[PDB]
Length: 232
DNA sequence: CGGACTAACGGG
DNA sequence: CCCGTTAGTCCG
Image 1 (cartoon, rainbow, N blue to C red):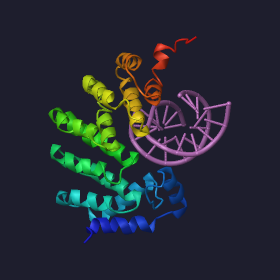
Image 2 (tube, rainbow, N blue to C red):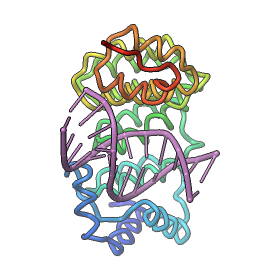
Image 3 (spheres, rainbow, N blue to C red):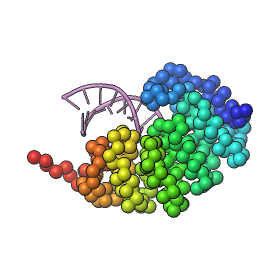
Image 4 (tube, rainbow, N blue to C red):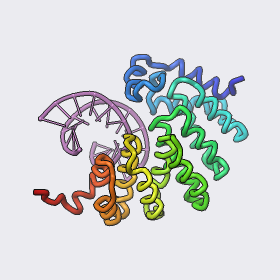
């Protein structure tokens, strides 16, 4: 039996569906998912409505509610699940890594994976850096582009706390990937980290092989700092 | 390739 | 208001 909070959310979202918007929204995600057609501002309000009426469920039900929402067809339910997980943030710890892994590799796409990785997993590994090597090597070795992207992006927001040796090691392992979502994640994490340490990122990109997309994205801004040499 | 543009979302 | 970003399409 579906949890009453999830049932209430399903009814309320469905009552406000927009088939006209659902079409372009589904196309944007390359038709991997059905959509109700509800964009983020309204989707968060509809969740708010249900929390106001029912109250947020006891923490004992947290993982259950996330999984039930994950199993519903329309993409807005996974987006809502992530909003709900943020509400239970203070209950999440290192013991939830496998739970988060399973979310990464089910109903997988860039929208859900990017919402799980730099935030929830990033925070966990900042608190428990000793656990990185229990997961990152397996992720990289896996057949799964989303675990590979997770390995790249978990340090995205680390700024001065970035483990540079680790970042570059991870990138080195994945630099030959022909997968767009890997090449782009490499570009993104380098571009972001260059905001903290431009010299290190510039040196890396000039001295290590990267896919063209990865390099181009990495230096999107810092090419202004260093210049674009004449090629002849 | 890589630049220009679109549309939505996060946050100064 | 602005800017920076996951994507996305389109054009030499």
